[PDB]
Amino acid sequence: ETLNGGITDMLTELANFEKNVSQAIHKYNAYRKAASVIAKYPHKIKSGAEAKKLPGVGTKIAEKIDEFLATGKLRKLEKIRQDDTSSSINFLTRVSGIGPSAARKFVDEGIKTLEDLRKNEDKLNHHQRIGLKYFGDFEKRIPREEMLQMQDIVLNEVKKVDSEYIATVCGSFRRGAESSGDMDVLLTHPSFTSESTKQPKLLHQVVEQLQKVHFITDTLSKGETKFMGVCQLPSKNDEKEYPHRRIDIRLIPKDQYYCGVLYFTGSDIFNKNMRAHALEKGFTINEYTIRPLGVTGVAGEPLPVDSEKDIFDYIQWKYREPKDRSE
DNA sequence: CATCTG
DNA sequence: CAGATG
Ligand code: NA
Ligand code: NA
Image (cartoon, rainbow, N blue to C red; front, side, top):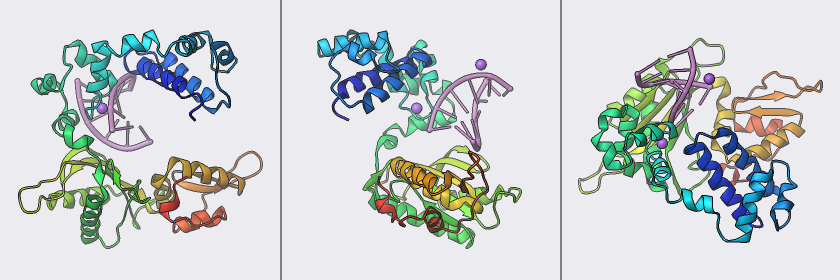
């Protein structure tokens, strides 16, 4: 956790790089298990050889750990931190819609900057365009004070369109959090479940309203169950308009809301712990259900949940307010 | 994993 | 349809 930090750090720098610049998934994947094991590792890695002793730790990494331990640096890391190419890739990637893949193409075409991009707005697609247009806004966290205001609009509109809708804003917002990166809504309806053959309108009607009133400004991707867009809190009395924010809305069969709701709410750590506890309790959980674990190895049959309560109940545990869902 | 692009 | 992105 702090005993082998540099190591684990350089290891991650390297890994990332393989994957983003080179195309080196194998290698990339290599650096990663390496950082992971050394991570769990209990002592002070004092040399390569000590390290090598670890699974996932080959001669190559070992070599690196040496130079690093030997000198506060690593030539490779040194070289890579300069290379404008590598940098451009790291940068372009920040644009929403531009992945590494794209980042590679663009660079080879000489587009390495924000300006480069605007100039070539033509080579970018819709997402990518939007993503370039709100680059600033997009990196700006979202303060609860706005989140509450956002949440308020969304729920009220959902309600209007159908009294029977059930919306929930998950994420850290849900666990208390002072700010957040984007708004995530879970949506369901009675008339929508496991079996129930579709009802696309279910998502689309809401989306529509949200744009009706102007809350939603752009569409990143609209599917029949997942919406990826942009919204904005109406600028009050002109002087201070709000940054554009990412927002997503997803339709879920009512018969599997809570697990999802539970699930999305995190944190990753709270999940796992519960997940692992579920297991003890003779259960299983995943993003959509909770199944009674047979003994034959495994077994299924989705246990029936009407709230986040039912879930906990099942694994016989303490209902935790979302705030305490930390770890 | 679901959506897009081409 | 593969392949890319979130
Ligand atoms: Na990106
Ligand atoms: Na292939």
